[PDB]
Image (cartoon, rainbow, N blue to C red):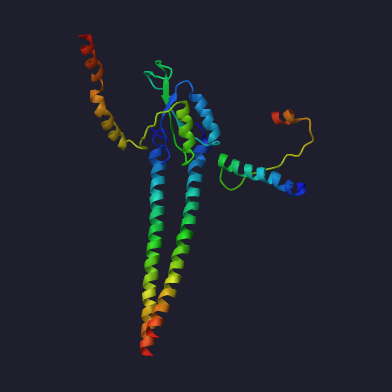
């Protein structure tokens, strides 16, 4: 019946699903890399303390 | 025939176009509207008539907006219908409905003879 | 205060339509858009065409 | 209408599951990477200080 909504429904659907997944990817990357950094900071102090 | 937000409910046979235009508006030029008239019209109690009723099927990305959808529908006319977007659960629904279906019709004939005698 | 609120008074509706069109129609990013600037007394006149 | 769901919502479900699994595996394996690299760093510092 209506062609343009047929056309753009999944276009917009996937575009915004991927925008949401991009926010998700940046969030997971940020938090996991922060985990990496803080974890290295945690371990280095522990080892240095022990062996000092 | 179809096409986590799909809704289903009873829509007045006559007022179908009113709903279609209200949708035309509320969803702002984006809709997937599929409805068919219901043969064998049905009864009611609000007006207590053998009314003429239809049903609706629509999909769209609104998740919280469905609040307004169901609210307006019921305030006008609607019967909640938890449905499935495929025909697999169709079998489950057939089974569950047939459960009561097998016996429903007794009530009347049972009630008859007692009051008669 | 008047001159300050001038710009935003219509920036708001600019963005309103900016988004209403996209969600209404067509591909996400952008479309042709313009502002109408005409003398008065022809409102229904223009609105017809 | 007839079976547009069969395609569109099947794709939507598969994409949703895939993106959520992608985020889960990314955060998981990034955490494991942080833990393993932390183990390597602590071992390197431990052997350094033991040599000292």
Looking at the image, residue A5 sits to the left or right of residue D5; the answer is right
Residue B47 at what x, y percent from top left?
43, 17
Expressed as whole percent of the image width and height from the top left, the position of residue B31 reads 50, 35
- Please indicate, yes or no, whether residue B32 appears anywhere in the rendered image: no
Say above or below: B107 vs B34: above
Locate the C terminus of chain B by quadrant: top left
Residue furthest to the top: B117
At 49% from the left and 56% from the top, the residue drawn is A23
- Give left or right: position of D35 versus B98: right
Q: Is residue D23 visible?
A: yes
B14 or A44: nearer the viewer: A44
Taking B26 as reference, is A36 above or below it? below
C22 relative to A46, above or below: above
B77 or B89, nearer to the observer: B77
Q: Total number of numbered labels?
A: 0
Horizontal and vertical percent for residue A3?
A: 52, 35
Residue furthest bottom in the image: D52
Q: Quadrant of residue B92?
A: top left
- The structure residue drawn at horizontal position 26% and vertical position 22%, both measured from the top left corner, is B104
Left or right for B106, reference C46: left
Query: In which quadrant is the N terminus of chain B drawn?
Result: top left
Q: Which residue appears at 46% of the width and 63% of the height?
A: A31
């Amino acid at each position: 019946l209506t062609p343009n909504q047929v056309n753009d429904e999944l276009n917009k659907m996937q575009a915004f699903i991927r925008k949401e997944a991009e926010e998700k990817a940046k969030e997971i990357q940020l938090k996991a890399d922060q985990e990496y950094e803080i974890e290295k900071t945690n371990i280095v102090r522990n080892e240095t303390n022990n062996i000092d | 025939e179809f096409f986590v937000n799909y809704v289903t409910g009873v829509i007045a046979r006559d007022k179908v176009a009113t709903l279609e235009q209200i949708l035309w508006r509320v969803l702002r030029g984006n809709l997937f509207f599929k409805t068919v008239e219901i043969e064998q019209p049905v009864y009611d109690v609000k007006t207590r008539e053998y009314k003429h009723k239809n049903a609706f099927i629509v999909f769209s990305h609104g998740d919280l907006i469905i609040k307004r959808i169901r609210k307006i529908a019921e305030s006008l006319d609607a019967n909640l219908y938890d449905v499935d977007s495929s025909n697999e659960g169709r079998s489950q629904q057939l089974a569950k409905v047939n459960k009561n279906l097998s016996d429903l019709y007794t009530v009347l004939k049972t009630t008859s003879t007692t009051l008669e005698s | 205060a008047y001159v300050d609120v001038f710009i935003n008074w219509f920036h708001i509706k600019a963005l309103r339509v900016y988004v209403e069109s996209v969600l209404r129609y067509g591909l996400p990013p952008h479309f042709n858009i313009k502002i109408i600037a005409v003398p008065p007394k022809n409102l229904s006149k223009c609105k017809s065409e | 209408s007839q079976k547009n769901g069969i395609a569109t919502l099947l794709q939507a479900e598969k994409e949703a599951h895939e993106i959520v699994s992608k985020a889960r595996k990314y955060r998981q394996d990034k955490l494991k990477q942080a833990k393993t690299d932390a183990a390597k760093e602590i071992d390197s510092y431990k052997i350094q200080k033991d040599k000292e």
